[PDB]
Image 1: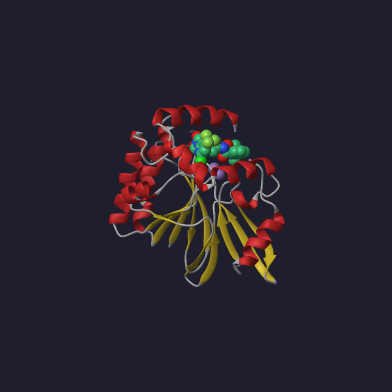
Image 2 (image 1 turned 90 degrees about the vertical axis):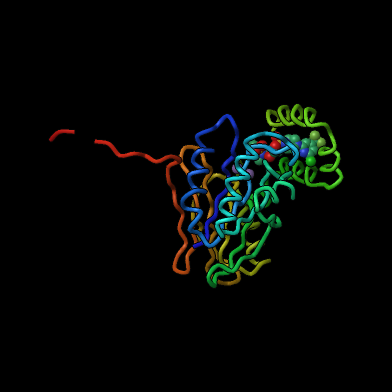
Length: 239
Ligand SMILES: CN(c1ccccc1C(=O)Nc1ccc(S(=O)(=O)N2CCN(c3cc(C(F)(F)F)cc(Cl)n3)CC2)cc1)S(C)(=O)=O
Ligand SMILES: [Mn+2]
Ligand SMILES: [Mn+2]
């Protein structure tokens, strides 16, 4: 089986989510054929030179899954678009483009973070166009670390709408697929539509707010799965 997760929004202020992700990496992830992280792994990112210890802890935990034989892939989200090749090397992850077409046990499946499907939010799209401009990224990354931290703290306070239906059909027909997996919208669901004159499905991941969420693809089915962060130890009413 192949696993997909997204929108964990890891941050030091939310240690329970970090604990849940480490348990996931130590258990379920080790049995997968591959692990895809479709964006928003971190709540924020200001560059791979950030000494934030959470970054090194996450990188080591993912690297252990990679060393165990499970290839791990990453597509950027709107929160962590500055994740670069230095962190990819530390974690063992492979960085993918904003859109990729996968063969999963015969299925042609398109994957993306999903924010590019939100073509009605012109305000966010203008932000995305700016922060994805290469010279703007290079200029920001050249700033001192403490300056970048101050900018990000203010910009987070300065800065979710849903996808546009026609944008979904356009992407699914551009890639000629009947399956699409994405996150960003934080609305876990399975939507049936029509693309390429045939039934098609858009599978949406959930954010790691109170419980975990993943999509598991097998040769036989597609599974949207919700699970608790930590080991809920059972313990023991009247008639
Ligand atoms: C969907 N959302 C939005 C909806 C509408 C609009 C935006 C978003 C949105 O995604 N905003 C957002 C994303 C990441 C962070 S950040 O803290 O991680 N960080 C990243 C690096 N970053 C700069 C800064 C610059 C420069 F200073 F030059 F401007 C350049 C460059 Cl290249 N990167 C500083 C900030 C902070 C805010 S929403 C509800 O916010 O989630
Ligand atoms: Mn998200
Ligand atoms: Mn997002």
